[PDB]
Amino acid sequence: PVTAGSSSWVDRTVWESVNGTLQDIINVFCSGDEAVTFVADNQQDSDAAD
Amino acid sequence: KDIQDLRTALVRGYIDNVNNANYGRYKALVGAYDRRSLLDNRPGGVVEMERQDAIDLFPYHNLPQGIDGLLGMSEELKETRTGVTKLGMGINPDVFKNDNAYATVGLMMNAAQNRLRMVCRNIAHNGMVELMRGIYNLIRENGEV
Amino acid sequence: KDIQDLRTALVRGYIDNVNNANYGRYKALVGAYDRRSLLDNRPGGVVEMERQDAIDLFPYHNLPQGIDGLLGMSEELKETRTGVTKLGMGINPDVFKNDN
Amino acid sequence: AYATVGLMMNAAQNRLRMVCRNIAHNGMVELMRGIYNLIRENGEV
Image (cartoon, rainbow over all chains, first blue to last red; front, top):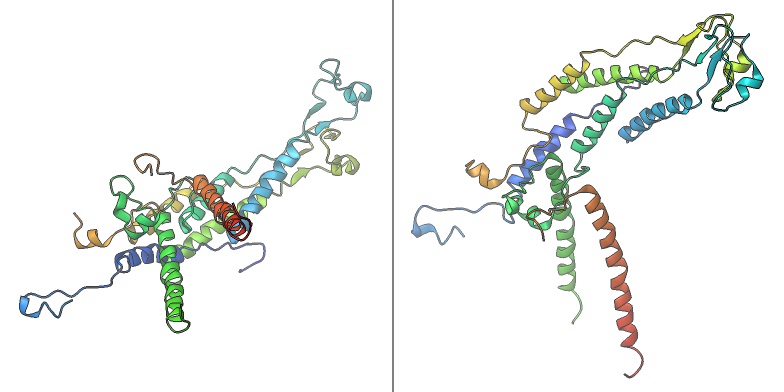
């Protein structure tokens, strides 16, 4: 507040974009009940994927 | 918090302006009082004597032309900064589990809706789930039912 | 960062303008005070004497006509420079794997 | 229930549904539980 008469009302903009990105981030990764799931390329090693 | 205060101030301004304009004070000269006629407030019989221009309405200040812009800015800021909206459609558990549950028309891809879904997901993952896990570890470690 | 600061400045400007316009100071001459009548703020009884033009509203500066343009420019710049949007539809894992 | 056109996702509608849910969970349900505990602990009908 450089001066009292100025009444420097701040504009919270960084917080806004941070939340706008974080919501989508969590909706991408943490949306599913699970996190990840390994996948193999052959049947000889599929028993270990699950 | 600030927003609230801000709005109040603006509102206050508006209010006081009206709170003065409703008084409707009249400016006048000296040789045109005619108290008997002036105080008498009836539709007909007034005496605006002494050149017919000795009386006029008090020139009150006009309303700030930019106030409505600030009101709209504050409103849209409250709307987008949080998950609130005047006519926003309420969320449901089905969409919280899968936003595309109503992908036909309820895409739900609104800034406020997602800002709200994020906080609800935070509450769920840091709240209810921990409570249930604790209750399970508790009932599983005491008592015979 | 800059955007934020910028907006604040602009906002501040706007604010102070209003923060003055709401005072509504009145300009007047010397031979028209009539303190008893002026200080009395009631709907009726005021005395704007001494030629009827001895009093007027203070001529405050008008709001900058180009401020709203800068506000809109900053808003669209925040929107396009990053992935944020007021009513933008949130993304999902399915589309992240296949936009189509 | 009417997701076709009655999404109901309006600020006022949800603000009202919240208070009705509060009334239900803190009102009628407690009344019924109390009546059940009462009738279950007295009388022979």
